[PDB]
Image 1 (cartoon, each protein chain N blue to C red):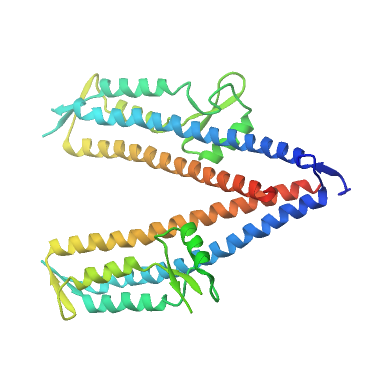
Image 2 (tube, rainbow over the protein chains, first blue to last red):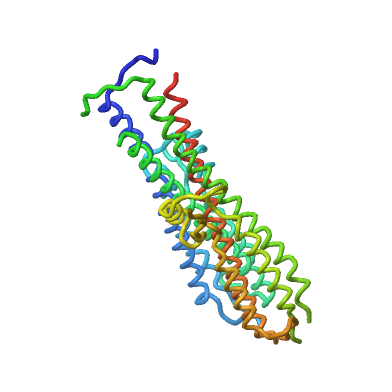
Amino acid sequence: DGDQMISHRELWAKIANSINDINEYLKVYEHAVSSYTQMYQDFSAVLSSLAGWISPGNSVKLQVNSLKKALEELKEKYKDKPLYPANNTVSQEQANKWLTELGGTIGKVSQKNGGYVVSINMTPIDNMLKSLDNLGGNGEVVLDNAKYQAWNAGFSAEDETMKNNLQTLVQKYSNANSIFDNLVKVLSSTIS
Amino acid sequence: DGDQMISHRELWAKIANSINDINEYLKVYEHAVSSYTQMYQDFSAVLSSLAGWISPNSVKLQVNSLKKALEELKEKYKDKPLYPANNTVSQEQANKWLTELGGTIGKVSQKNGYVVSINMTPIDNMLKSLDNLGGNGEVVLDNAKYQAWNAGFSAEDETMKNNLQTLVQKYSNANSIFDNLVKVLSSTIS
């Protein structure tokens, strides 16, 4: 039973196969971080442009159509850029396994071509688009210093929501790298 | 070289030997985390007692009360080190583990025999920052002086907090390497 023999040559093949299996596991994390960094980058640009989209109206006059147009273009930009698998698609239970691995809030499962993918969770974008529409009025809307301060607080709260979501995603990727590094060091130091 | 054959029993043995070797890594990490955690818990207790040492518009500070508390914490952990938990090791044994854990978390001391004691440079900086304050116990400081001192005091606190956090992460990462290696050994059998 345990008398079956294998060569050193066959072991290195089994090691190299498992090495490639973990590398593609890391490249999923690598792409997931890269696409969420870009999404947060473009979002932070919308928040930096906010200063040029507000003006005095004691109160302030907010250009809603300019801000809503930028968020719509941002949501449309990452409609076809998912966190995983960046190409083709996988099954539904497979996408749910990666959603739970990456975090439920940072990702969102959706199907594209029969199968399913893990698209970027655009809930803070949707929440920012609905909060604007509830400031009833075509074009620009005037709000007192108190209401704008509360609306701007929720805007910065969603911005910090993405900032910490990205930081934990980077930490998981950094941890997986160190776990892979020492794992390869261990497997090589054994047959050395 | 590559034509050499090994049996399935030698496979299970070769994996188990590396698993017992990495378990010795976890034995060091587990204790070192436990020793630095108890120190930061005792230090966190001193922070909870800081509210009773400041009082009112300037502030008053029982400098000698906080000084003796910090100095007692260091003397408590002067003999309780990070590694080894018992006895001692060689010089290059403590230096290799100092580099593994980080040159900032620990300090290599000599016992007849070397040991990696807990690095107390944050406590030393706090004590000199307190000694730079006024004399004879209680000290009066305006709001500006308390803002600056508490800023550097919170910085040294956050330094130990980050030191403990990164050490736990290495221990969590080192445990998952043990877990994954166990998964391969269990799969090879059957």
